[PDB]
Image (tube, rainbow, N blue to C red; front, side, top):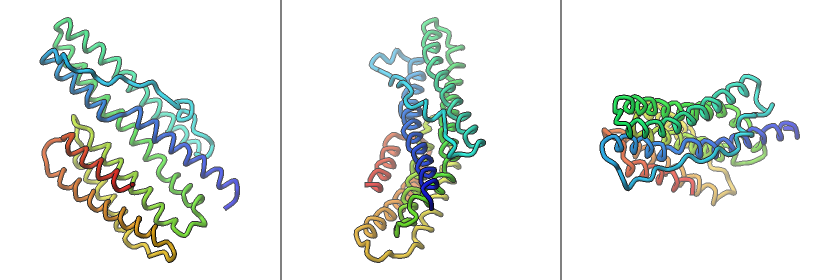
Length: 256
């Protein structure tokens, strides 16, 4: 591991961290759910008390649209394509909301319903582009970690926490798709999480890191609790915010 390797690896992780924040901001799943819920309700009643969450201005678009040469050209292309597609779908989704309200003002329920249906599809697309970006990055961030943790006696444990935390967040982001739940996809990701947890459970005790070992095994126990909760929620027939918040809370406690 040279200084060039280290810089490269840092740049990869930098881009991931910026991406995590940007995608959190650009697809706020509960806000998107809220927009769609208001659209549905406004077609039934005036829904006079509602204030739908406004679309925040894009931050760090200069960074995410310009992935560096720490990624290969194909990767750079695919990242740019997915971000570009995301920003376009999001623009449309929010433009369409305004137009929808104007069709309703004109009593044009027929055209309003069609624009609602288009927005359900744009919501799914936004979420797909977001997950696509994480999926693209995953192999490269794993390589970057190996460089940065090369001399760290807890590299395997550290990497397992980072990997499983990403998988839990991916499951949360799917679960939040209230209007178009992909049950089998959630099950697939729970099976990935389970494989990660099985791998983690094989790791040895590292001598002289008594606190870190305790911390790590508490995390593993919480991951197992999370897996079991997601399975129980998957036996139910509809999304609920209570279930989402239970799961997100289970996640947050694991990373404390």
